[PDB]
Length: 94
Length: 99
Image (cartoon, rainbow over all chains, first blue to last red; front, side):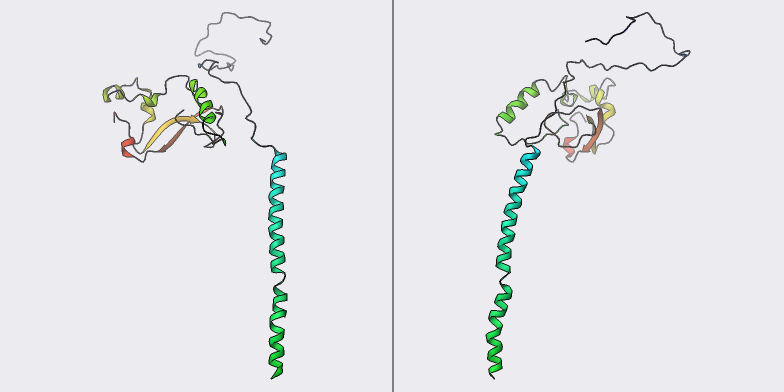
């Protein structure tokens, strides 16, 4: 599991002012790796397929309601022509 | 613990509470310092107090919270860099007891 390395370790005694070829040490945190929990991708409760099914069912319900509105609102011209024509004839009777 | 808020999970509040129980058993790796208010004002003012430099204005609190995380978020705690966030201390009595 350990990444491979030709050099095990050596003894280095750094100074402050004369760090020549200023490197970038790999910093490490101080909290134990036991507190650093492993990652888990929390899967969503629903799937996009179930989303499609539910949204399509809702679209079917909305379309049924819109069709009901259409059949109730398509007769209004029929009401117009059923109500005024007898009255227009009555006015013509004068 | 005291800075993260989660989501409802469409549950019976028993299993939903239940899982929170064991996730809480180890959620705090250490002492959350915000529960240590038994100390007197003398102990509080002392520089060994860590939360001193997280108190700069009476109207707000200063604290560490997950960064780049929208609250509330998924109940499983996301891991990110710790950052500093502040809130409104509306209640004047919410000022720390030593103060």
